[PDB]
Image (cartoon, rainbow over all chains, first blue to last red):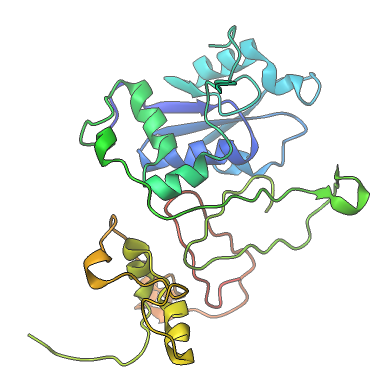
Length: 96
Length: 96
Length: 96
């Protein structure tokens, strides 16, 4: 069903993270979630096919802004694409 | 008068999907894969064929306590029971 | 070929409300109170103005065990977590 995108890493949390995941699974796309330490129990982590901790050691918000860690995880896991969601890094030049 | 462009999905995209019939988040994915709006898979009608159907309202349910200056409450949610029936949509954040 | 009339609401009325926009159960109530289909409060369009919008599917989730000849299971439901997002409707029976 999809040309290039076989796996999406959803670089957000909460509601919008779940929305994207649900759209991915509808299109037969594999999903990868990220969570901060603080969000180890957020339920968006249980909605993806894979999940990985991000921002280890950073503050709660900074952890979801860790561009290079997000890129590491994206690459490690085989993610063709990243959906940044809204807020956080969604409008951030360096990240795009 | 123009005031702003947000180059991202928004929280309220939900209400637009409801009156137009178009899955905005799938569309996002389709687009970024490389497709074109009207490719039969992506199914976006031509501008002439996009219409308004009914009206939709969004309410965001948050732990902001109105009896305490809208300060966000914290803790375990012991009971969480949402709702259903015709004309109702729920997009869950960290309320489970 | 005609075969039957059910003089009542049906389980699947849901899918009709979804493609036509018309709350069938409210309509029932309005009718029995004494109103007329098109009274502006009841808002039922004229036959010409009633249309099909999209398509809808209904699946009934039951404790019928397919690995045991569809015999209804019983017991406490320890976990029950439904779903959400765009295009999704839930009408709960004794699943909470």
